Image: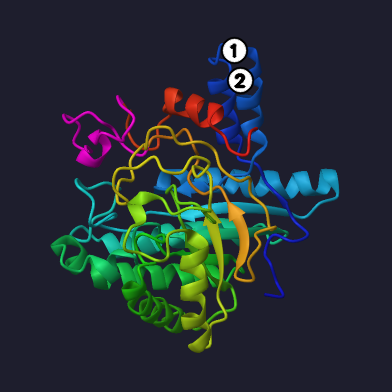
Amino acid sequence: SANNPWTGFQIFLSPYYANEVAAAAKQITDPTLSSKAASVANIPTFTWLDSVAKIPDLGTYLASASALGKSTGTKQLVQIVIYDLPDRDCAAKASNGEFSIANNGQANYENYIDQIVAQIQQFPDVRVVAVIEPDSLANLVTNLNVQKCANAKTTYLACVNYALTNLAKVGVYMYMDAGHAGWLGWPANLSPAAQLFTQVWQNAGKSPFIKGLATNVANYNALQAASPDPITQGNPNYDEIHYINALAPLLQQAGWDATFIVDQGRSGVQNIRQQWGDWCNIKGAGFGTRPTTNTGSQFIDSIVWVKPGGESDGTSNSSSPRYDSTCSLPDAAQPAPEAGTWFQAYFQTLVSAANPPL
């Protein structure tokens, strides 16, 4: 579209990932690989606001970005993920996240949004791009048979609506999570998905700040694959470009000329999964195409790195209360530490297998 949120802005680089990366690179013994690993701290990633405890980090990043822009003659852009729904990840094995529907979850979530808005309101010279709630609305397309998802449906919709409505008031550019080609890109899921996303967009007032959708977040699909990965058999939309090319016109017809961002942070290596739904710490993943607005598609504003490669997707320890058996599958790297915590061996392979090379 005319207004690509990234054009003319410098992306604030996460100091946490830079340090996570910095601490990781000092442990890599081969000096050539260690220096490549260190350079990952210069690659922009999204900051996950996965709990209220992360909100003060958001405030510091906004203030730091504001000062850095003045120091360098640039306009700065901070990239965040809104990821704290009550009864989060309703179709996953085991619960996670600080809020529950049964304990004031929606109200607690709206206070979480209010705290985020109150930070963003203080720093109007910094642009913010937010991915809205990975692993949420897509469950309301295909997983309404999962009782936790059926019981969460009204809460997910109300909470996402509150986030969109209130972040728009402070000018945040938003992309709702929309799964990936192997989730919502199946031709038969496209229209139900479009109908859901359009209803959500309508309920939040069709704000121009609701730019569109984010795909492949925390996943591994190609943006454009020369040959279909065998996991995709049966789905003509075998990569993210096919999915997006199919979904976008349905949104346009509703009056929403939606644009997209696509995670490629762990997409450098294709054909590494037994089944398409295997999502946890997939072994042999490599860093993929670096973030860029040179996307090759009318519909795609940016290739992005949303999930920060090197942070675990979940523990492989079946004794943890947070254990999801997906993280013990044959194509999952093991042993793996708790979600969001650093998985050093996985990071080193992401570096070694990066494609394009680092």
**Is disc 1 placed on a helix, strand or loop?**
loop
Frontmost residue, 165 versus 274: 274
The magenta segment is 313-335
Residue shown at 59%/65% (left/top)?
172
Within 10 Å of disc 1 (Cα), the crowding (few <14, some 14-19, many 20+) is: few
In the image, 59 versus 182, the foreground residue is: 182
135 lies above or below 162 = above
Identify the residue under disc 2: 33
Q: Mark 1 points at which residue?
A: 30
Residue 89 appears left or right of 296: left
From this viewpoint, which residue is outermost toward the right?
73
Q: Do the residues labelled 1 and 2 touch (CB within 8 Å)?
A: yes
Residue 53 x/y as whole percent = 42, 43
Q: Residue furthest front?
A: 227
- Residue type at mark 1 is Asp
Query: Does dot 2 land on a helix, a strand or a loop?
Result: helix
Q: In which quarter of the image is the N terminus?
A: bottom right
Is residue 293 magenta-colored? no
Using residue 200 as the reference point, say whether residue 168 is left or right of it. right
Q: Quadrant of residue 200?
A: bottom left
Q: Which quadrant of the rendered structure holds the C terminus?
A: top right
